Image: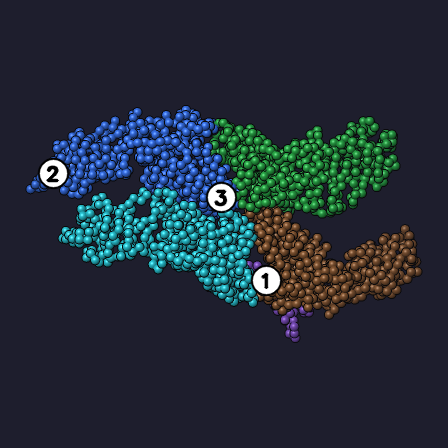
Chain colours: A brown, B cyan, C blue, D green, E purple
Amino acid sequence: AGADEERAETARLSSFIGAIAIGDLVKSTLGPKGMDKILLSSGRDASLMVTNDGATILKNIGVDNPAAKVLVDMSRVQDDEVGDGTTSVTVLAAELLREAESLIAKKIHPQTIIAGWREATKAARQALLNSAVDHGSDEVKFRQDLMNIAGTTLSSKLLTHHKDHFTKLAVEAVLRLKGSGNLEAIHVIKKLGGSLADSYLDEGFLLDKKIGVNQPKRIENAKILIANTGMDIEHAEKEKMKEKVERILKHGINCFINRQLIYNYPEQLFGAAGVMAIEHADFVGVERLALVTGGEIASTFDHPELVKLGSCKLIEEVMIGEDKLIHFSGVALGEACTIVLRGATQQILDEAERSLHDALCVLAQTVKDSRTVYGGGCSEMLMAHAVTQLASRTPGKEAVAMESYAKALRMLPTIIADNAGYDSADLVAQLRAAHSEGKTTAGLDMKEGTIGDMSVLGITESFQVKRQVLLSAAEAAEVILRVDNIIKAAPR
Amino acid sequence: AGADEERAETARLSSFIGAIAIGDLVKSTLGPKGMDKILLSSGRDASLMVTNDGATILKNIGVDNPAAKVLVDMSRVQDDEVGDGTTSVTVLAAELLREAESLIAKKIHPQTIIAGWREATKAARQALLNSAVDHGSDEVKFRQDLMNIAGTTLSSKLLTHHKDHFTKLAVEAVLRLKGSGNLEAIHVIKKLGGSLADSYLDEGFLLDKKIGVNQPKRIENAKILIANTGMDTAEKEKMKEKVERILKHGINCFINRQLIYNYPEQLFGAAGVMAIEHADFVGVERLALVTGGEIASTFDHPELVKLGSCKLIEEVMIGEDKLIHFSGVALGEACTIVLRGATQQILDEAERSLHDALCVLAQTVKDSRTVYGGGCSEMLMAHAVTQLASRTPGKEAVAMESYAKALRMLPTIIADNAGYDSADLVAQLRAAHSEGKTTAGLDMKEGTIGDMSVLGITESFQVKRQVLLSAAEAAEVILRVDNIIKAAPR
Amino acid sequence: AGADEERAETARLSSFIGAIAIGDLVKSTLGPKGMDKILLSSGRDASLMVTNDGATILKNIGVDNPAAKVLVDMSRVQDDEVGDGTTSVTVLAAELLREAESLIAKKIHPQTIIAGWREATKAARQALLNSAVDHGSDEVKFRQDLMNIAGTTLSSKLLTHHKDHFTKLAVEAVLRLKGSGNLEAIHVIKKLGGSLADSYLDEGFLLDKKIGVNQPKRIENAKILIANTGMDKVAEIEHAEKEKMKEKVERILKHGINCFINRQLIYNYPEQLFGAAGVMAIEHADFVGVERLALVTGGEIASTFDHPELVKLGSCKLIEEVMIGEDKLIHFSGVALGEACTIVLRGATQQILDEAERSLHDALCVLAQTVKDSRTVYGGGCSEMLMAHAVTQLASRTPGKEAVAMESYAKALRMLPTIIADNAGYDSADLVAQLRAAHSEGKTTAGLDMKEGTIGDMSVLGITESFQVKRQVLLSAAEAAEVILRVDNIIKAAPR
Amino acid sequence: AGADEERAETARLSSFIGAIAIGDLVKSTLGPKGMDKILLSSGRDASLMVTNDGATILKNIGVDNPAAKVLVDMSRVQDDEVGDGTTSVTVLAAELLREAESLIAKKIHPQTIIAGWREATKAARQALLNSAVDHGSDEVKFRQDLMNIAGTTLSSKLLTHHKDHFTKLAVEAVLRLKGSGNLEAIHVIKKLGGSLADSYLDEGFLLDKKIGVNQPKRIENAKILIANTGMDAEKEKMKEKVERILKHGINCFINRQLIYNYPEQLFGAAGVMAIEHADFVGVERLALVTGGEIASTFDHPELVKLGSCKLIEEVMIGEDKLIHFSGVALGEACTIVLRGATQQILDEAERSLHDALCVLAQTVKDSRTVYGGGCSEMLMAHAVTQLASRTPGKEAVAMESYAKALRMLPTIIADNAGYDSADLVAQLRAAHSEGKTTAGLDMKEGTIGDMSVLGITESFQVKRQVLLSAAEAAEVILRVDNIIKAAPR
Amino acid sequence: AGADEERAETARLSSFIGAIAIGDLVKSTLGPKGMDKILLSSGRDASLMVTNDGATILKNIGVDNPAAKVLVDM
């Protein structure tokens, strides 16, 4: 009873406890019926932060003494190349530690057990495409573009009553995204007001800056000017003023965008002319705009006329249910487009700044991968039936490592059933029988409380989440299990 | 949170902890690789006692706050009609608690789960007699009398070097005592002197006493007199009544259970009669069944109301201690085994094992059925029970599967106390049983798997049927009782 | 603020700790230059008890909570079938625990190693029948009466200088004693003076008492009387006292009474009578001597003054009060029975002369069966080195697991040569290697000669060990100590 | 001062405790079944660092009062000029301290026991000398150059899935440098940019620097100039440098310090490639390669300078620009150079090439190796046990205690395999006694097998350094007189 | 008992409490005989604002640990 001082057995437990504590908070977030949580902290925190995405909160806060923060940091790298959907990778790693309890009972070299990871690779061969799956999106694709994985990513997120519609909108954005040059030039801004649609799709670019209170409300047959150099004895200044206007009247210029500080003198002049300019426009938006507007060659005040190409469908500032912004539309190119999101309404609403970035990635993979797997636990039960056989028929050493890996899969069906509110035990017996039969389409239906046809619901998981999780699941852990717990010092 | 008031889920956990703690101490006492343990206490304990037998130590002390004393008390009722062998019933009852963790996931009501226990009855019935119990042990029996179950009882006891030979001797004792209808006339004394044989079998009853330093050494065509009332009590009249009745009978030996009066004693020496003073009553009762008995009352006791055996009564040196031998009983039903041994705590240890060796063998003759030991029975049942869970509809299936799962730990427990990797042992073990060989089991000495029959290890059939149905009913009452509230006695 | 708090590996330590504590006290005792320790306790203890014999002290006291009393109890059975010599069985068992530190390093299954204990069954038995060389003793035996094992038992004792002579004396005591009669009525005492002999042999039983200053110097064809009850117109009553006197003298004369011994106070009137008559009486005689004496004299029925004549059986040879150099003591001697006999050692109130009494009981046991066994082995550790050279071979011979346990047993014999030499006052390191070469060569007689400072001929010295002590020690020790390490953990829980 | 004064048994104990703490952490790290380890520490570490190689972690941190740090420090000297492979030198040294508890029973003085070390030589020498182990290493050798010990050093480390091949490359480097002692002038670098083989072999030395944006890309029949003093009226310095330079035909300038701007303009037009703040370690090694020169003041060019004129150029081999020095006339010194895939594993390759390099140079020249998997150790145990009986008075005590120590090593290897060592300990003993030096513990087998088939051989140097260092440390602290102040610093 | 530690079901109660706490202040305002509330805040606030309009006051301040700010914004 009691005692804190780490050597031998105590060493494993600190890592063991860290893994179990995080699993309960993340478990609620999995699949179609996930949950949203709020957190409050003193240092560099304003109020409770509610993030649906597990990865965002783990990076943000280092709450306590036990070791687990380093494991958390690594997940971000995964996010850049795929990331989100639902947070499941951390959970599988945590459950790996649970049978370590059985390891003391084993009473043999813990490190020998590492051969189990090699064994896991054997499991991996068996794991690979043995579980029917779904063929996936051809490229662009009609119906299969969405009403799939994005909805699942959203399911945990607190907005899915109307949000699933929003997700459906997002695949349209990804299809246009491919071809130009991987992923950049994507920007979306949320709106503080609610509507049934809850989102508008723009054919151009969305920006939020204004020259000043004075100037005409809207421009047509717009000409766009982009300058690298700022507009920045007093009589000599007037010459700078005049050159700007002289070149400007001739073109018919409707809008001027400059990436940096804008000199005050021209501003007075623009208002009389009827030309709208933007001060300190961000470079990333501008560069994107150039693709959209046909581009410009930006240099010194010589920049006007022919060296400048400007799209002209329409540039205007449009009131959008509350916070108004400038909309660039009708781009001749058509290659780059912008999405405007409207939120449920709350602190959660501002996540839309970088939420889309997480959203773009799951949809982009679905269209790009051209492969998928069946949703709501369909994949997990089928694989579990196959793995149980494998341990029994491999004699001696080979059998112990494979069997332990196999039971890990059983918990996932239950986690989905438990968040459903239906009985987990009733669910387990019925679930296994349908998968055993051979119907890969059949899966967990939370709404029913019983097993049903997953395909009818339309919930499917993309192919990348299943192959990648399996490859490094057994590689990240092995460096750690090679070790018991840490070297000399007198920690904590 | 954290301070002793318990309700619902917190109440269940205390029961859970008590079961796990007991299993680790008892596990080391299973089969051929079992071990001896010594416990020390202060306050009405005398000091340090060693108990190989799990049941004896558990009954003696209620050590701490967790609740398990009542569960412990039950094992003794089992012991008189079967008991011992090896202690396995407590372990199986304890492991049933582990499934309760999966139970929280079930999250509603554990009670309909109980239906699983009757499902368990099919599993219980299905594999313990399904391999090859054996056929025989019809009566007295030549070779098959031992080098079987007694050895297994001894298996849990390390002393089984010299000791397994001792075990072999015990069945000879059971053949005369067979029936177990009435267990009585068996007396064993350990002797302080080392020898390879370690024990001697006496054709009768062994007792340590002498009249005094006078009186004849040996009697033949012996007549035996036992008196309920003492010789203690004009005095000459008591003397003459005793002599007159005595001479006609030819009285060879007199045994009295209490104080003896001196006047009689002078008489006995000249007469040629050997008398015993303050002989223990329990020996006397056993003796009565043995010699046809007698009615013990006042000095009218001699002649016909008394019956006496006619073979041989003499005092014979045993090792380093002087004892008297009663033998040649006409009845033949009751006889005595005398232990010798090296002499130490262990020699006193044999006292603990006597009332263990005797019970197991008695049961083996009556059941006429047995199962393969060394864990052979346990792995086979596990393979068969896995199929059953899949067959049954749903909720029942969930409960049926969990019971099957528990059998897996036993192969592990035998290997774990043996000295070989538990993980490696399980994989190789299952393949042997799966194949179809009943004889094959766990060979602790080997470190792998082998033929159990060669070693001579078998388990009584009766221990296996009783453990299965009884465990179900006992487990059923604890899940059913959720609220346990108690305070310190006084 | 206290507690016992121990788990898993610490539990192992409790078995470990008991063995180390016992070994340090006993090691000094072993061999020719042994050490004597006095133990004093209060509360159901009297004073100054010092025991040379390791077995006697361990049995008497259960000092503390850790387990060790049970291991101790085993040694007494060994003592019954052969006895002592020097205490060594406990020491070897203790060192077996040291390998367990190695066992954590082993880090597999400590119980698997326990298989070695099974192996020890074979290890102990090859130890048997094999080893030391000697022969037999016929009966009575002139030269071979002693100058053998008693010197060996004594070697542990600080006593062996003048005392080896005392030891020689003890077999004379056994020769008169010999038979299967028992070890009965053997009494030996000590006296406050210094002489080369340092001891004397009394014909039969020693008692420190006298009737009074007056009375005959000695009695012959003596009759011995033992009484349970004590001797304890106005003028006629004084006359009546004389009546008690009358019965005592008139029937005392018919018997021929030469000595009266009473275990209590004695009335003064009879005392005058005994002196004139020629009869020697003893006031407040010790009861323990009396019961023992009765076996010697054939006994008697001790009741009221009716006690004389036939109910009394006195043995007659010589009862006298004799000079023991300083003070004077009375010798019963000449017992017809022959079953019981006595010898006298000299020292008294020295400091530890009472340890001699403790020393004495174990020493007597050694001599009594030397004649009965008729078999012995060479002393001075000659027997121990030879067996040790042989056992190294054995560990290699047994496969796998068995070799580790058998090899440990072999090193146990090595320590004895070192202990014998170390207390001698010579360098232990030099002694061990020179010793091994002589035994290896093939000479059984050669052994450790402490006075020499090197190796010498044991047979000339007169030091031997009973064949029985070596056979039994190897069998019983292995099987009995087997029990101790078969159990790794001894615990329970908590009190408060 | 500090004044921590050591007394008899309380002096010995500090040495005893240090040895036990090190052994448990290092034991799991050994050979094929070797494992990576992580550490979190007080003070300035703030996080968990993972180093497979035991030596790297021990030098970085000096955690507590007893001094084991100095024992630790010694292992690096071994690592730079021989070294690693598997960490066992520290483990064997630690195990000998346990016996000292036994030694108090002996109770004379430690020094008498010290006789064991003369006999450590006789018992052990027989042990190394029990023979086979080393094929012979003829000199260079077509296939025995590797796929042996370097591969095993890598085995404890993960990079081995594709880096076993990298290890193979390293032996080629050692063979060309054989003779005149050992190691000098060996260096290794890694480049970001993937290839399946993951390596490029350079016949010369690899340096990562460039003169500037301008200057000829490739130089031919190059002359090398090394200056002890930096380039840093001003025009006169410019004039002296140009006049001397043209006659020599100087194609490259290497200076170990800061370089002045004026000469730089001249070098581009001249056709001479110069290197700013060149590393001294590369230069000294390079000097053996180019024949060297005496570096003085600008008077230095021509005869007082000796340059090698084969081929110097800066080559784009992938991503980061590097400069290749090639054509060593001496032949005594060469480099190697490594490539990768662009992975964490690749940077680990840098960690183990050093490990591979040191082992082979010593393995080839010493003409000795030992059988791994405990083959050498059990055989050694059998020979030593009879030896104690053989020795006289003062000889027969020290040797006997040393002999039982060897017994533990077979046991440690069997457990890390996972099989029961009890069965293993004497089954193993019977095979060594028989006469097969090639037989030993087979971790993969789970019992005993043929070590030679496995291909695990240990450098003879790794085994001598460990055994001698093992108890010398034990005997020195117990003796310690008039200790002064405290802390290794 | 004795602590403010809360999880899952007890956790729900804090959400529960926020809704009840807001209702008592607002109810007085809801009709033809309302009260009037002032609310003075210390730290980066300009004077105490006394508001009879319930919507205006809930939006202006995020007073404490319990969560109700998000309900208010809509």
User: In percent of the image, x 48 and y 35: which residue is there?
Assistant: C393
Judged left or right of residue C267, residue A167 is right
Q: CA distance from mark 3 to mark 2?
A: 78 Å
The quarter holding residue A46 reads bottom right
Q: Which residue is mark 3?
A: C113
Is residue B385 something one can see in this rendering? yes
Q: Residues within 10 Å of mark 3 (few under 14, many from 20)?
A: many
- Kind of residue indicated by mark 1: Ala
Of the two numbered discs 3 and 2 on the same chain, state the one appearing first in sequence: 3
The subunit letter for the residue under badge 2 reads C
Q: Dot 3: what SS?
A: helix
Judged left or right of residue D480, residue A53 is right
Q: Nearer the viewer, residue A63 or B67?
A: B67
Q: CA distance from mark 3 to mark 1?
A: 52 Å
- Kind of residue indicated by mark 3: Ile
Q: Is residue D14 above or below residue B203?
A: above
Residue at the extreme left = C233
Q: Nearer the viewer, residue D254 or D399?
A: D399
- Kind of residue indicated by mark 2: Arg
Q: Dot 2: what SS?
A: helix
- The circle drawn on residue C251 is 2
Q: Which residue is mark 1?
A: E8
Is the same chain shared between marks 3 and 1?
A: no
Is residue C1 something one can see in this rendering? no
Q: Is residue B464 above or below residue C268?
A: below
- The circle drawn on residue B163 is none
Q: Position of residue D184 (x, y in %)?
A: 71, 32
